[PDB]
Image: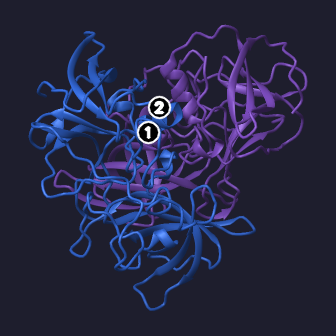
Chain colours: A purple, B blue
Amino acid sequence: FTLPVLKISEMTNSRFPIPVDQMYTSRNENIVVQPQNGRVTLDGELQGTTTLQPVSICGFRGTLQTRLADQPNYTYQVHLENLDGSPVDPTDEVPAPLGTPDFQAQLFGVISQRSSDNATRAHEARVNTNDPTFAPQIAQVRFKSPSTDFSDNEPIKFTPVGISVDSQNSYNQWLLPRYGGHLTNNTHLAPSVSPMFPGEQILFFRSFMPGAGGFTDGAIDCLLPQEWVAHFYQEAATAQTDVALIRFVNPDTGRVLFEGKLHKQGFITISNSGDHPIVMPANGYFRFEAWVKQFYSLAPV
Amino acid sequence: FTLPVLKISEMTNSRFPIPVDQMYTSRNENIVVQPQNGRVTLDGELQGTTTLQPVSICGFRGTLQTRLADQPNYTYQVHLENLDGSPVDPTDEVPAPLGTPDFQAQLFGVISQRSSDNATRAHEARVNTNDPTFAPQIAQVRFKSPSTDFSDNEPIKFTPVGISVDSQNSYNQWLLPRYGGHLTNNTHLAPSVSPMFPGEQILFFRSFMPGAGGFTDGAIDCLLPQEWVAHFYQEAATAQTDVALIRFVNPDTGRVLFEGKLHKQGFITISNSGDHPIVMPANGYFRFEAWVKQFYSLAPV
């Protein structure tokens, strides 16, 4: 069993298409940690809405249907396709199309269009993933743009950039959208994750999304870098036990700086308490040490 | 020596942060093919402006200096930094900061800003990589935005989305910007690439960039998918000869469909003539076969 040897700054957040900025740990009391992007088992089984390419996270494609005249200027109805262009089939055993955002926010980015004659246009757009009409599982999503320059019945692509916040639009990275819209309950979710030994917390790979209005640090925490997600999918290895002991090494000295448990479900725990960055030499990377058990007692970080 | 087993549909273009759409070949007569992103040797030596961050290709970080009142509404001067936050050191053996676009276009995307109090703002922006003032090698780049809403001395990020084309802004994917600006000549370039054997052409991984105005198919051709770039970098294998013979296998039949020459310089040649997509079974992928000599003779198509 192997891990990619990439540095923190050479890897991509698996929940938003930006580089990992830091490792981070927190207690997350009163929160069910259940991200749907960046979800893979150590055996390589993708879960949730996880896509393989980083550049597709929180992106979507589809067809622009109409401008909704009786909605705030200017709101448009989109009929989603899958990232591969195929029709969204709600009977698929996924919570929503691959790439769908897995958090509640005013998601900010650009809607672009290309016609059969290769005419193009693109403008800023915001997608409210906490609106009742947000129903990507059934292929219906709206965006709001300052521009009227969008063409009905032509293809669209959403390129995410960041989030915007205000009192009417909180950013809750741990609260899932209702992918079916309105009162529907989510289905086929990748399972929640929790540390399962006293003294342990999950170790996150944290990035700070750009903001497009309001005060926000944009912090978003993923369970595994996207490069690990694709690594495990490709390796399609069989986990020997439920827990791989991994060690964070500084290649400048070859010494181990700390260790963690890489769980079969696809997340890391460390022996540590509190909410804070885990600050480490920039060249450090994790390497697999051995298969162990849930009760392996980690050296405190 | 190993090659990743990803399908075409699972690949990222290494010259723009979008998925690969198709394999593509062309003659490229009268063109020095010398892309600077997506450049690595089979030994793992990164070249040109290649960044390991796939989402950061054609993106950049820096500091907004001022709005330039003498220029078209609204033009801002940026002092670049590197993608990893380190300052640009122009004596680095690179043509320009890692991630810099390697083509002449009006690049379209979003400039986002975060203030010291975590206030944020973001607006669409265009970067003309063919303007004489475009001088990323010495950390000077301008962008034009329809918004006046940017703050001086605060950090910015450019998130690329696509290109815009019009009478004053052609898109030439194979013509490099003058990274030093004005009349200066490029330095530290990744070498040009060319078939060296009768009947061979380069095999490219082609994607279609979003457009933000004008008629354009947005076609952009990379030498290696970003996943291979990162793989060769991490493996740092030894190229036993100057050419790895690679076989395109269809796992649906288990049989080889055609052969390519994967050159030590980091590009593929095939026996083929003309400009067209190379359409193959969707599950096919390249597999390393053997280390061969420069003059190994490939069978057609």
SS assignment at label 2? loop
Residue A45 drawn above or below residue B197: above
Structural distance between the alpha carbons of marks 2 and 1: 16 Å
Task: Report how many numbered discs are placed on residues in the image.
Answer: 2
Task: Examine the rendering and report whether any part of residue B188 can be seen.
Answer: yes
Task: Examine the rendering and report whether any part of residue A95 can be seen.
Answer: no
SS assignment at label 1? helix
Front in this rendered view, residue B239 or A67:
B239
Q: Is residue A176 left or right of residue B178?
A: right
Query: Badge 2: how crowded within 10 Å, few (<14), some, or many (20+)?
Result: many
Which of the image's four quarters has the N terminus of chain B? Answer: top left
Disc 2 sits on a residue from what chain? Answer: A
Front in this rendered view, residue A163 or A1:
A1
Disc 1: which residue: B229
Residue positioned most to the bottom: B70
Q: Between tags 2 and 1, which lies in front?
A: 1
Disc 2: which residue: A52
Front in this rendered view, residue B271 or A165:
B271
Instruction: Tell me the quarter of the picture where residue B144 sits.
Output: bottom left
Which of the image's four quarters has the C terminus of chain B? Answer: top left
Indicate the position of residue A107 as horizontal and vertical percent values. 55, 51
Disc 1 sits on a residue from what chain? Answer: B
> Residue at coordinates 12% horizontally, 53% vertically from top-left?
B29
Q: What residue type is labelled 2?
A: Leu
